[PDB]
Length: 257
Length: 257
Ligand SMILES: CN1CCc2c(-c3ccc(S(O)(O)N(C)C)cc3)cc3c(c2C1)NC(=O)/C3=N/O[C@@H](CCO)C(=O)O
Ligand SMILES: N[C@@H](CCC(=O)O)C(=O)O
Image (tube, rainbow over all chains, first blue to last red):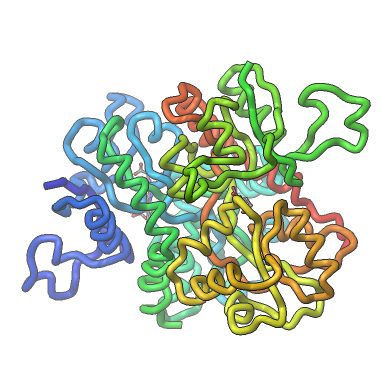
């Protein structure tokens, strides 16, 4: 029985409204829930879904240099695999094995429909329409370390923008965009931006291209034999068109706009 | 001195206009020539840019079960690493090592302006306008192993159409689209499709969205010690935004069309 570590993140892994009457992996539904099922069938193994304790994805603490989240639960032999929207990064790659990305993404711009913004350069060229990110995370860090002119300017603006353009959560960012009457833009993951875009009141949308390129990947303990079989699974699921099917399923079929 | 095998596919790898007045790797230019320079810089090693002998990307022969193109040169010990627009595929993942994707792409359609086609389905619904792909390419491998209605049908057509709708090289396919008077559509990766569309004589065009989603990856023989190093360098060059830089530098459209 393979211990699968994941995290509650809609539409990846969520609990059904009636998860009370259900039990086991049946309580959950979502993109990663179906993917986990597909990976297990192509690899031939029984799995049990568990939610990462600290609700973190994976980061090494500067102080204790200890890994937390789903990445930590892997490097310390607590879980056999990680099936969630885990982004493939250098530091992470160094401590765990990553299969080829099962979904692409990148920092994108979320504006309230009607907002006269077309790209990142447009935002950096003005201030009448405030824009921000999470007051903590990779999105924020992305600008704090960007050598690109457009992004470097955006960082200077944001860090000195008044009132504060940083939000504490994704919910706050989305709500602020919906309440600012087109006077505020939020920078978040494309997958999450295009997901909200399919949710009523349907007043938001993604604009322009992503400011960068990332990709989620299934993770296994560095050196785990299970990693190879899972990688081929991903590639096969992608080639057969299944990954595009699961995407269209939880993002558009269940759409609302 | 690491031996790097690559293919002349512009804007990835091309021979400088005055290459005869040059020598060494300095003879070439392109996205992959730069990427290679960066990979070698970080991994710390000398290299030589060799061109794939049989001028193919890679494909296994059903009967002999022998690989050709770059995949072959890596499998049979002819090259230490492959730095070119090599598509990461299941069948290739099984015989060679791949680094995480350094660039994304998807099969697309190239046509001569005025061609009554604007989607893969349109082509699959007729025969007046012939269409094929590149030999020993991942695109041809796609349709052949595809079980997705439209694609499965397109494959059947292709291997039954007369004369042969297939071509030996990308240029051979592009030239056919321009000379066929619209009586031939070419299926090639969007990356190469969009580049050529912004170039003279400005007679080709990309229609409809891509048919799939994947990405090019750095390849090395299985077990190769370069694998890890190169992979981490790829993830770093991405996080540093170096990949996007090269992407914008070589795909920069100076409005010829
Ligand atoms: C599809 N999306 C959904 C949200 C999300 C969040 C995420 C979680 C909470 C929130 S919040 O509730 O609004 N908040 C700010 C508390 C916002 C974003 C964080 C991470 C992530 C994803 C995937 N993938 C990662 O690799 C990752 N690393 O995350 C890193 C930390 C940040 O870089 C890690 O956990 O190591
Ligand atoms: N990228 C393909 C070649 C181009 C194509 O098939 O259109 C490969 O690596 O085989």
